[PDB]
Image 1 (tube, rainbow over the protein chains, first blue to last red):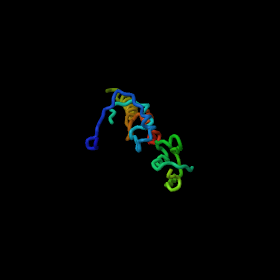
Image 2 (cartoon, rainbow over the protein chains, first blue to last red):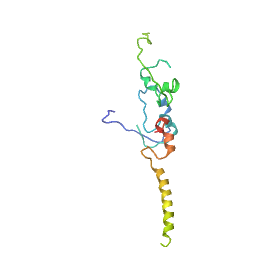
Image 3 (cartoon, helix red, strand yellow):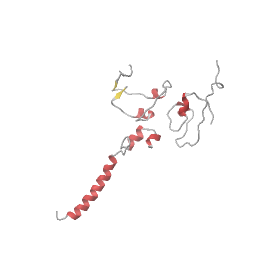
Image 4 (cartoon, rainbow over the protein chains, first blue to last red):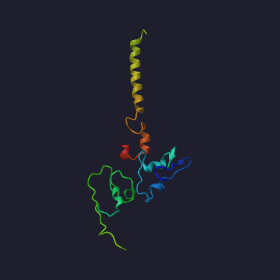
Length: 50
Length: 49
Length: 49
């Protein structure tokens, strides 16, 4: 979607492998703010939104 | 320490960075002191083939 | 209220201990007041801060 009508998808009830996101070189910017990128596999979350 | 990398990978030669050559090729410590030097070498380290 | 002088000392010491315990719940500008949350969420360059 366009940026004025940006699409919000709920992520819930899943096990997430962020290591395929860290190890992929396709992303020009992979920058996390309130959490380390390598600790994402060690934590549990709710209210995940893309 | 001399090496050749890409143009977008020069941000990863720094303390406290997350990245690819930082993890598996060349890591700088968090208490690193010194200077990192980078310049473009497309005229020398590149071939048309 | 006959024994208020001793009870005042007891209440002051217990209140000072309660304030000192309560001060652990404050984050003092950090992201969390729990050390384990910071150590499990962040890399050491920003977890140090």
